[PDB]
Amino acid sequence: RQEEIEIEVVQRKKQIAVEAQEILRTDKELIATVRRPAEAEAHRIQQIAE
Amino acid sequence: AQRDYELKKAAYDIEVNTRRAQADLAYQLQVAKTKQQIEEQRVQVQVVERAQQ
């Protein structure tokens, strides 16, 4: 059982490296889904205001 | 003559019954002592299990 529970430990040890890529993925995803679309929506206003 | 024999019979029967009672119960005593050592290690697994958790 010491060796069996160690399987869970190495899984967590790797899951940490998975979530490290998840942050980076979520960051780029927010640039494409939030930051850039909002910047486009703001330009419409500056044009239709004229 | 009967009495002389009857008393020795009863006297020897005390010892035979005494020694038989000891031998009869001698097994379970060791079973308890052996389990005493076993249980220590059965729950020792819990300590090691928790330590990895």
Image (cartoon, rainbow, N blue to C red):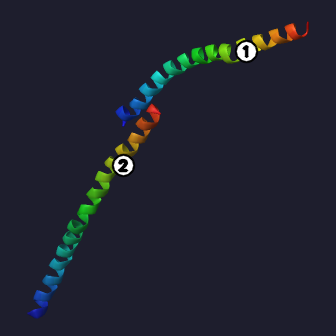
Quarter the N terminus of chain B occupies: bottom left
Q: On what subunit does the disc labeled 1 rest?
A: A
Q: Please provide percent x and percent y for residue A7.
A: 39, 30
Q: On what subunit does the disc labeled 2 rest?
A: B
Q: Helix or strand or loop: what does disc 2 sit on? A: helix
Q: Please provide percent x and percent y for residue A49.
A: 91, 9
Distance Cα–Cα, label 2 vs label 1: 66 Å
Residue shown at the point (28%, 62%) measured from the top left: B28
Residue at the outermost bottom position: B2
> Which is nearer the eye, B50 or B17?
B50
> Which is nearer the eye, B21 or A9?
A9
Q: Residues within 10 Å of mark 2 (few under 14, many from 20)?
A: few
Residue type at the position of mark 2 = Glu
Observer-side mark, 2 or 1, equals 1
> Which is nearer the eye, B10 or B44?
B44
Residue shown at the point (63%, 17%) measured from the top left: A29
Q: Is residue B9 above or below residue B49?
A: below
Residue type at the position of mark 1 = Pro
Q: Quadrant of residue A30?
A: top right
Left or right: where does residue B22 sit relative to residue B35?
A: left
Q: On residue B39, which mark appears? A: 2
Q: Helix or strand or loop: what does disc 1 sit on? A: helix
Q: Please provide percent x and percent y for residue B27.
A: 24, 62
Q: On residue B52, which mark appears? A: none
Residue shown at the point (76%, 14%) measured from the top left: A38
Q: Is residue A48 above or below residue B25?
A: above
Residue at the outermost left position: B1
Give the residue pinned by disc 1: A37
The answer to whether tags 2 and 1 share a subunit is no
Q: Please provide percent x and percent y for residue A39.
A: 76, 10
Q: Is residue B19 above or below residue A36?
A: below
Left or right: where does residue A42 sit relative to residue A37?
A: right
